[PDB]
């Protein structure tokens, strides 16, 4: 796809297992002859390799260069998969290639799920790290005559999990900030063993003892970046989008976001003492700001959870006046970093009118009192 | 100074950084030689292994049973959007739910051997633009187009003939593909290319 | 081995009792079995106590659940209750450790230590309270110890108050007002029963003096003590003594007592009415006049609901 | 009576005024004609005025007085009614949760679809929750749970075996999944008092539908295995908390055949 790479139109896989990449240039009516941009060789280990020999047609490339190779030796059938390590790929390129369990003939491969690619531009297309949360888990289909095999991509969280006992390796490849972020997610992550959560909490809070230290240096510590990255990634889809059109996002989604942020809110609230309370002070300020932000998002989402319950649409239509243009082009972030007066008026209408039912209504009145 | 604005700025900056991330493929990256973390052994890359095998589902015997007798031709495949698998033995075709397996659908419509099957998107503006996907089936004689959909009540699979038959006797349609324009291009064992338009007619692109 | 163990509870066999006893020190299952096994309360309790005291890792939450269970079955009692008290302290210390930001996650070891077992009071005090400056905990601990020494007790109080000052910024005069009252009331509830940690006489002025460098509303100081669990009658006599005893202005005391009397009369129906509104605290004690004529007998202690 | 008492004011002056007030207060109390005297049903739109309100004023204090008294007697319904007028929304739901909560646990054969505590439950939720709801989230949550359990009852019996499982699972109270039965233990003690009481019937409802639905069929995809695993997890659950339950693990009777 041009989204993945503007220049590269096609990839050819040979019987040898060599991958050829060709660039092109279209126009409204004329194609351009393809040129061979690059070539990749099979790892026997390296180049002269006959490991991939022979390679069957079954082989296919998964959007964002994930290579599934079906090889039929002249002794048996072998399956290999190559996935670029996106993380180190945040500059150098590296591919992790491993053998796979399937031994039977491989009829056809397909992707059960959309591709994980983050952006629709060559820039940040491949960042899996960013869309690890949002993008659905990647699942791959291998069809054999005998049965269907399902393969699952391993997320960075899983990688960290394996590494839980040594996380330097994650640190090395991925970087400290990312390690912190994943560490935070594991700590919060639900159905996890206490050992895992505690260890991840320990890493997040203290890093590795007498090894990797967790710190602001005369920039902000990895902890801050990790937490912020986490927050940014979850919200990334919704953040820019307009809140109201009916609400742009569905109720299920609202509940999902609210629940997730709630977990984070509680987490930070609980271990706020550690983070808060000059590089050190700057870290304190930054963390304080982030925590306030998480709570604020919680509040906005909470209100929306409320609105979903009922008769929101009718009031909206009747209410909107001259201010309306401003209202409609309000983004979620606008709520995140609030536009207080309009909401207050609207909320008052929700209460004044019958729409809010029972417990909900009490809550807004509480809200207006508290932060209004 | 305000923390709230401050936090917003931090996230936005980071978001920007995430978006800027380098392009996946560059010739410069492996101009000398490829860095490979390649083990022959499963789970050889302990922490790193990109993929794991979650499960294996065998073809249901109930499905297989109606594949027992096949003189002429066999073929099978997976439909990516459907999350269903298909099996073709001679004239008949089966579709089976990936997740279930018990649930299978059978086509009794086709009289003749089935050369090829394919899943395609509907055209922008025909009577069936609404349907999510179309199933193209080619036999020696004809090409049939049906509609696939999911019942919202049962959540079962609904197949309806969108009676559209295209005579393609000579062709021996080897391959079928589509552009999401809704245009369908197929090739017979007759050289490189042909294109179908439902609005039946076949027109060779590569000129007859 | 079969994990048939639950069935074991059922077995009547006279052989069974000695079996459990010998095996008693995944034995914990045997013991969960044992206390349950004992229909008798006394025997059951003795086991859970040992269960809690035991050297295999068992979470404090469980250790306490054992005690909660053991206590329910209520010198054995003596040991059990002391245990509950000390265990509770660790829970508090443990909770604070989470909030504290001075701590490092990797020094998880402390939590492991806390949940792992009951600890020496001195160990808890010297090791935890002082280094982590948990003044409240230290105070509570010394309550249980029953350490009387007023200087040490007071000195500890001074630190708590001083620490409180540090965090405050001023806008939150009210905010701090609440937080301050909140902190004091909590500790106050635990200690207030005993006079040594909670010298009401010594403490009240100390608090007023502290808060004095803040915006003031009358009744702010006394209300906390009332909430603390101190009775209206107790507060009254001591306060009156403070009033009369001091050679000085105590405008503050007069005001607060004024607020106290007003607070008290409304709360019980007994005291209620007219001779009162006039009262704007002085030695024009409404109660004092009442006492002279009828008698000193107020009534039973009145406490805030 | 109200009309006559009102004349008392005709003698203008204090004393008489209080006498009037006391008389009305005395009338409300012991006559217990709250709706007529005090008012009724919000449908938003505050109170629909009672006869006295038409006359007006001290009416809130009388309500608290009456309501508290209702509490002594235990005349629930009157209390709920009184608190609604009081506009103590949180209090109403809480009393309400209690009323609906018991009567839920018990023995079956009831609940016509039209009037009573359940019906009362429906009234309040629809009524308050949409509108600027002043109640605690916690209070409302238990409220919804009680309603969900009730709808489960309606459909439990009157057929609809399949539907009952779906709803019960939605409750997220009982382990349908794996051996996560124990997590259901950890989250059990935490449970509010109102629900903690109700679980007995939740179990056994499950083993019932589970039984009847899984009547061994006659003569193909039949996954009997599920709706079987569910019973298993449920039994482990029941096995873990029998002591903290009324004492009817006669789930066993329904369990087997």
Image (tube, rainbow, N blue to C red):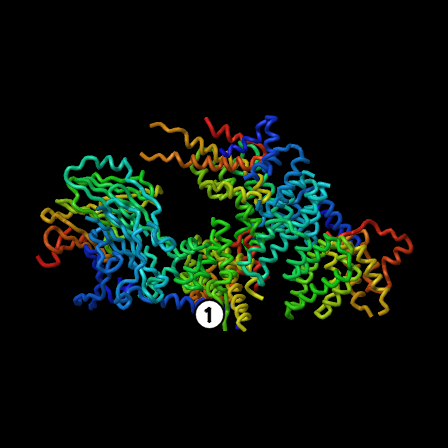
Q: Position of residue A138 (x, y in %)?
A: 34, 53
- Left or right of C170, for residue A185: left
Res B127 seen here = no
Camera sees residue C168? yes
- Is C134 positioned to the left or the right of A241 in the image? right
Say which of C274 and B135 sits in front. Answer: B135
Which quarter shows the C terminus of chain B? bottom left
Side of A242 where A108 appears, left or right: left
Taking depth in this image into account, of C45 and C23 the one nearest to the observer is: C23
Q: Which x, y percent locates residue D148?
A: 50, 42
Residue under the point 29% across and 53% down:
A81
Q: Position of residue C207 (x, y in %)?
A: 74, 64
Res. B23 image quadrant? bottom left
Q: Residue furthest right?
A: C293
**Outermost front residue:** C22
Q: Is residue B101 left or right of residue A360?
A: left
Which chain is home to disc 1?
Answer: B
Badge 1 element: helix
Report the residue marked by disc 1.
Answer: B9
């Amino acid at each position: 796809e041009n989204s993945e790479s503007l220049d590269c139109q096609l990839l050819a896989v040979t019987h040898a297992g060599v991958r050829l990449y060709f660039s092109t240039c279209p126009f409204r009516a004329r194609p351009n002859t393809l040129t061979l941009v690059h070539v990749r060789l099979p790892p026997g280990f390296s180049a002269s390799s006959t490991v991939e020999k022979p390679s069957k047609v079954h082989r296919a490339l998964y959007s964002k260069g994930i290579l599934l190779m079906a090889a039929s030796e002249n002794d048996n059938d072998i399956l290999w998969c190559v996935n670029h390590d996106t993380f180190p790929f945040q500059k150098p390129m590296m591919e992790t290639q491993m053998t796979a369990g399937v031994d039977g003939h491989s009829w056809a491969l397909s992707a059960i799920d959309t591709p994980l690619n983050k952006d629709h531009i060559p820039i940040t297309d491949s960042p899996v790290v960013v869309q690890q949360h949002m993008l659905p888990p990647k699942k791959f289909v291998l069809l054999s005559a005998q049965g269907s095999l399902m393969f699952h991509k391993l997320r960075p969280v899983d990688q960290l999990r394996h590494l839980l006992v040594e996380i330097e390796r994650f640190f090395k490849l991925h970087q400290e900030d990312q390690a912190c972020a994943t560490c935070l997610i594991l700590a919060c992550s639900t159905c996890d063993r206490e050992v895992s959560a505690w260890a991840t909490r320990a890493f997040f809070r203290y890093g590795g003892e007498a090894q990797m230290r967790f710190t602001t240096l005369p920039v902000y510590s990895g902890k801050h970046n990790g937490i912020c990255i986490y927050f940014s990634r979850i919200m990334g889809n919704i953040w820019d989008a307009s809140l109201v059109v009916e609400s742009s996002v569905p109720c299920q989604l609202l509940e999902s976001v609210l629940q997730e942020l709630k977990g984070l809110q509680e987490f930070l609230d609980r271990n706020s003492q550690f983070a808060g309370g000059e590089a050190q002070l700057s870290e304190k300020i930054s963390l304080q700001a982030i925590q306030q932000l998480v709570r604020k998002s919680y509040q906005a989402l909470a209100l929306w959870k409320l609105l979903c319950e009922h008769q929101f649409t009718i009031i909206v239509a009747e209410l909107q006046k001259e201010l309306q243009e401003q209202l409609k082009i309000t983004t979620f972030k606008d709520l995140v970093i609030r536009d207080k007066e309009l909401t207050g008026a609207l909320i008052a209408s929700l209460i004044n009118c019958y729409i809010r039912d029972n417990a909900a209504v009490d809550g807004i009145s509480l809200h207006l009192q508290d932060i209004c | 100074q305000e923390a709230l604005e401050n936090a917003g700025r931090l996230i936005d900056r980071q978001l920007q950084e995430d978006r800027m991330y380098p392009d996946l493929s560059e010739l410069l990256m492996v101009s000398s030689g490829m860095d490979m973390d390649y083990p022959l052994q499963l789970l050889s890359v302990p922490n790193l292994p990109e993929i794991s095998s979650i499960r294996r589902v065998p073809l249901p015997p109930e499905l297989v049973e109606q594949f027992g007798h096949m003189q002429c031709n066999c073929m099978m495949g997976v439909f990516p959007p459907i999350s269903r698998a298909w099996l073709t033995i001679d004239s008949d075709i089966f579709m089976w739910n990936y997740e279930d397996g018990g649930d299978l659908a059978y086509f009794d419509g086709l009289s003749e051997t089935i050369l090829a099957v394919g899943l395609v998107k509907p055209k922008a503006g025909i009577f069936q633009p609404h349907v999510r996907h179309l199933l193209v089936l080619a036999t020696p004689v004809d090409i049939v187009i049906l509609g696939l959909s999911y019942a919202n009540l049962s959540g079962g699979m609904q197949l309806l003939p969108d009676p559209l038959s295209l005579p393609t006797d000579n062709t021996y349609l080897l391959t079928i593909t589509s552009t999401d324009n809704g245009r369908i291009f197929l090739a017979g064992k007759d050289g490189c290319l042909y294109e179908v338009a439902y609005q039946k007619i076949n027109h060779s692109k590569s000129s007859l | 081995q079969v994990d048939l163990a639950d069935k074991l509870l059922q077995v009547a066999s006279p052989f069974l009792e000695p079996h459990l006893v010998r095996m008693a020190k995944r034995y914990m299952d045997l013991l969960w079995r044992y206390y349950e096994k004992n229909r008798s309360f006394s025997n059951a309790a003795r086991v859970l106590s040992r269960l809690a005291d035991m050297h295999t890792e068992i979470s404090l939450q469980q250790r306490l659940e054992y005690i909660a269970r053991a206590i329910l079955s209520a010198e054995f009692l003596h040991e059990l209750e002391e245990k509950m008290e000390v265990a509770r302290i660790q829970l508090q210390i443990q909770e604070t450790l989470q909030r504290q930001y001075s701590h490092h996650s990797s020094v998880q070891d402390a939590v492991s230590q806390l949940d792992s077992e009951l600890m020496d009071i001195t160990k808890l005090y010297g090791e935890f309270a002082d280094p982590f400056k948990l003044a409240e905990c230290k105070l509570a601990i010394i309550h249980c110890a029953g350490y009387s020494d007023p200087i040490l007790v007071q000195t500890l109080w001074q630190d708590i108050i001083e620490k409180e000052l540090s965090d405050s910024v001023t806008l939150s005069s009210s905010d701090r007002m609440h937080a301050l009252s909140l902190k004091i009331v909590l500790l106050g509830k635990i200690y207030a029963g005993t006079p040594r940690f909670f010298p009401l006489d010594f403490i009240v002025q100390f608090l007023e003096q502290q808060v004095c460098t803040l915006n003031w509303d009358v009744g702010f100081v006394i209300q906390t003590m009332n909430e603390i669990g101190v009775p209206l009658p107790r507060l009254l006599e001591v306060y009156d003594q403070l009033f009369k005893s001091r050679d000085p202005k105590p405008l503050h005391l007069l005001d607060c007592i004024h607020v106290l009397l007003i607070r008290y009369v409304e709360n019980p129906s007994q005291v209620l009415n007219c001779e009162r509104r006039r009262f704007t605290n002085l030695c024009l004690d409404a109660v004092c006049g009442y006492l002279v004529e009828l008698q000193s007998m107020s009534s039973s202690v009145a406490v805030q609901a | 009576a109200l009309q006559y008492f009102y004349f008392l004011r005709d003698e203008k002056d204090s004393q008489g005024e209080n006498m009037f007030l006391r008389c009305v207060s005395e009338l409300v109390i012991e006559s217990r004609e709250f709706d007529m005297i005090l008012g009724k049903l919000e449908n938003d739109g505050s109170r629909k005025p009672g006869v006295i309100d038409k006359f007006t004023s001290d009416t809130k204090p009388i309500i608290n007085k009456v309501a508290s008294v209702a509490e002594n007697k235990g005349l629930f319904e009157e209390a709920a009614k009184l608190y609604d007028l009081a506009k103590n929304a949180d209090k109403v739901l809480e009393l309400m949760n209690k009323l609906l909560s018991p009567v839920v646990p018990q023995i079956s054969a009831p609940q016509s679809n039209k009037e009573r505590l359940k019906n009362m439950a429906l009234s309040i939720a629809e009524r308050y929750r949409a509108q600027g709801i002043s109640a605690n989230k916690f209070v409302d949550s238990t409220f919804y749970l009680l309603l969900d359990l009730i709808t489960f009852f309606d459909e439990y019996h009157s057929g609809h075996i399949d539907r009952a499982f779906d709803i019960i699972e939605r409750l997220k109270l009982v382990p349908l999944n794996q051996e996560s039965v124990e997590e259901r233990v950890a989250a059990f003690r935490n449970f509010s008092d109102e629900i903690r009481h109700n679980l007995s019937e939740v179990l056994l409802a499950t083993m019932n539908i589970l039984f009847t639905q899984f009547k061994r069929l006659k003569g193909i995809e039949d996954r009997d295995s599920q709706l079987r695993s569910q019973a298993r997890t449920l039994i482990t659950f029941a096995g873990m908390i029998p002591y903290r339950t009324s004492g009817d693990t006669n789930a066993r009777l329904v369990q087997m055949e």
